[PDB]
Length: 393
Ligand code: HEM
Ligand SMILES: CCCCCCCc1ccc(C(=O)O)cc1
Ligand SMILES: [Cl-]
Image 1 (cartoon, rainbow, N blue to C red):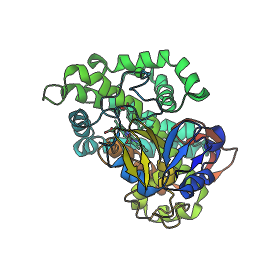
Image 2: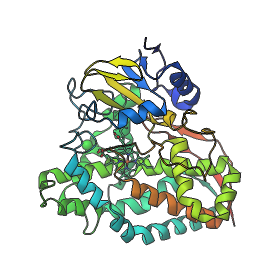
Image 3: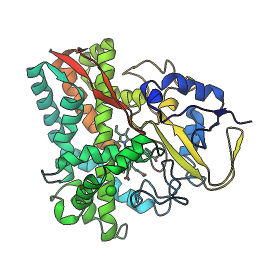
């Protein structure tokens, strides 16, 4: 009954252009079986949304990558939040939710905004820049490590460690194998910065450690929760901002709308997250036999959810393949959905908004003026290089 497909969603050809294969996956049926990796697949909005919102049946504690922690050893100690289920999930989720709170956003917003204006002003002096290294990477690097309370030395380890994390969710292909074999120095740096003495007062990391006395987490849980922010908190935003700039570069009419109303900045970033879905895919593991989209899935099966595909499903979206900065984006799954829905989304949206605000106010045009290169990663979608000429307003 369930269609079997030979599509490899973790192959370079798929990364290079996923959209036709995603339509093939959607149109084959609500649930598919991927013979390449022996996992179930769901690529339509309805089923992706359903799976995300049933954490009891589709659990995370057996891992959200291909590997089933009940069968294999996780490559690093499990995340206490991403790779945990309720109830163990709940209090660590609460702590990170308060660390990354509206009040915290209120404290850092003006610095985040100044840094974005300054970056755009600096890039306009150069004119011809690489929007990945010089903007999508440089801006988050200029605010997030400091907000974490990290020291200066060793920050070069952060993006490699994140690339490693996101590749390690994937199957054991060459991307994953190579990342792991290169991992040791990046892991060592990150794990050491997670210790209380190494996190500057006032920052996210220190605030996690300060929350170890409330009965929500214990002091021995705080380093791995800092580890979560150092895993998730930089590279995601890099590819998110990268996405938004690429969208503005490819859809000049939308840049023109954004210039005319800079208050559209926050939604213009949200749409870019829908449209490019920086985090493309991840897994759940079934804890029981379950009926999903008319198909029966046994206990202990991995299920692969295509977030980027759900975000382009014409069953849910009008003109999904158009970038529309005034779209009602509410309900997209680029940040997940349900109990694990991105706990860092206020930081993400803050960085995204103030960068696109700076662009809206200072830039007249964004023209690609060189070869675009894609970056391949088992989990993340984004570019290696985006040469653009910026014209000042
Ligand atoms: C555009 C940027 C981002 C995107 C697209 C993104 C995407 C996601 C998605 C899809 C999930 C759900 C994973 C799941 O359900 O298994 C998630 C969870 C999470 N994200 Fe984000 N994220 C972004 C930025 C950030 C930032 C800036 C931080 C930290 C400062 C962060 C930290 C986390 C953490 C700790 C979780 C686990 C939450 C939980 O399991 O309850 N993310 N993210
Ligand atoms: C790729 C499938 C999982 C979704 C990834 C979201 C980003 C993220 C990474 C790592 C951690 C962590 O807790 O370590 C938390 C979130
Ligand atoms: Cl690690």
